[PDB]
């Protein structure tokens, strides 16, 4: 199975005029990074709706993962589900990004651009989709096997899923945020895996990335304490090989230098009064 190269993009998919666009659509940058990390009860309830819809779009596209299919076709499906449910796909026009989800095969760490790329037997593909509705975002992702995937790669996927769920299950108010990345990295290193450092989880609410950073590796210098009403992603990228990467000329696609495969899972989480609630569930 050869190292991936860029396929060709389908044209911009329309979304109905009546679906509110985030402010950043059609602009070179977003107005984000200084928004409160704790959400009002109103925004939390709305994020339940956005997260539910993202989860559905994820589940739908992931159902179409099969040898023969294009990444572009996964995007079509995710886009349709978001649009049919009244949601704007948050990635569409986010800093110029051209599609409605990210599709990240094999050695693509993250930010892959749905295209003419045809999935083959044994590949793994991450699909990351975000919903914007009622003025808020919800983001979820998962890595899906295509065909007869090698044990090596199944285990990577299952272990990355597990790391993520372990980390989620440590979320509680009064606990150090740094606990997330300690749990993740300790679990990954157990199997000889390497945790991506340069890409992180983030606060999410009325803005896509509100400036809160959630590290997935052990970094006990972070002082941030989790508080009820905080909303953020946990989204570890976990590599079979070394952390060294390249970005393609499209400006988005992140690939492992060594071309070894990598996996990722993600939810949008609420810190409740007593623990956690996963917002990106069906
Ligand atoms: K990947």
Image: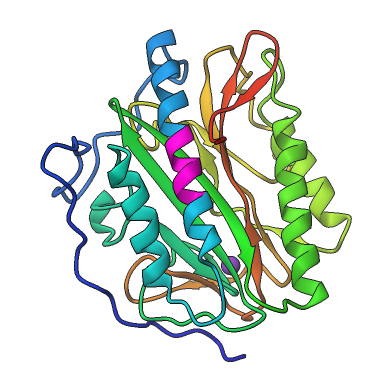
Q: Work out which residue is located at the far bottom of the displayed protein and give it.
A: 2
Residue 10 vertical position relative to residue 233 in the rendered view, above or below: below
Image position of 222 (left or right of 78):
right
Query: What span is colored magenta in the figure?
Result: 52-58
Q: Residue at x 62, y 50 (%)?
A: 265
Quick one: quadrant of the C terminus? top right
Residue 83's quadrant in the figure? top left
Residue 276 appears anywhere in the view:
yes
Q: Is residue 56 magenta?
A: yes
Image position of 49 (left or right of 20):
right
Q: Residue at x 56, y 80 (%)?
A: 67
Residue 181 vertical position relative to residue 74 in the rendered view, above or below: above
**Of 64 and 270, which appears nearest the observer?**
64
Quick one: quadrant of the N terminus? bottom right
Quadrant of the displayed image that contains ligand 1: bottom right
Image position of 165 (left or right of 248):
right
| Total numbered badges shown on the rendered structure | 0
Residue 89 appears anywhere in the view:
no
x, y (%) of residue 60? 48, 54
Q: Work out which residue is located at the far left of the displayed protein and give it.
A: 17
Q: Residue at x 80, y 73 (%)?
A: 152
x, y (%) of residue 59? 53, 50
x, y (%) of residue 172? 70, 18
Dominant SS type (magenta): helix
x, y (%) of residue 95? 26, 52
């Amino acid at each position: 199975r050869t190292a991936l190269s860029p396929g060709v993009l389908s044209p911009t998919r329309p979304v109905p005029n009546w679906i509110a666009r985030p402010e950043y659509v059609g602009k070179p940058a977003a107005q984000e990074g200084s928004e409160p990390w704790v959400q009002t009860p109103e925004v939390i309830e709305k994020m339940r709706v956005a997260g539910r819809i993202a989860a559905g779009a994820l589940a739908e596209a992931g159902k179409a993962v099969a040898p023969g299919v294009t990444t572009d076709e996964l995007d079509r499906i995710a886009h349709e589900y978001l649009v049919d449910n009244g949601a704007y796909p948050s990635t569409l026009g986010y800093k110029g990004f051209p599609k409605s989800c990210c599709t990240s095969l094999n050695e693509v760490i993250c930010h892959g651009i749905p295209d003419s790329t045809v999935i083959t037997d044994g590949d793994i593909v991450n699909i990351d989709v975000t919903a914007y509705i009622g003025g808020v975002h919800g983001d979820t992702n998962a890595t899906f096997p295509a065909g007869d995937v090698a044990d090596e790669h199944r285990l990577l996927v299952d272990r990355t899923r597990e790391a993520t769920m372990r980390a989620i299950n440590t979320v509680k108010p009064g606990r150090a945020l740094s606990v997330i990345g300690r749990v993740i990295e300790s679990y990954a290193n157990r199997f000889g895996y390497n945790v991506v450092r340069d890409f992180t989880g983030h606060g999410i609410g009325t803005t896509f990335h509100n400036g809160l950073v959630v590290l997935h590796y052990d970094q006990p210098a972070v002082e941030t304490i989790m508080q009820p009403g905080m909303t953020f992603t946990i989204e570890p990228m976990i590599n079979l090989g070394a952390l060294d990467y390249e970005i393609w000329d499209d400006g988005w696609t992140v690939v492992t230098k060594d071309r070894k495969w990598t996996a990722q899972f993600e939810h949008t989480l609420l810190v409740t009064d007593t623990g956690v609630e996963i917002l990106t569930c069906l």
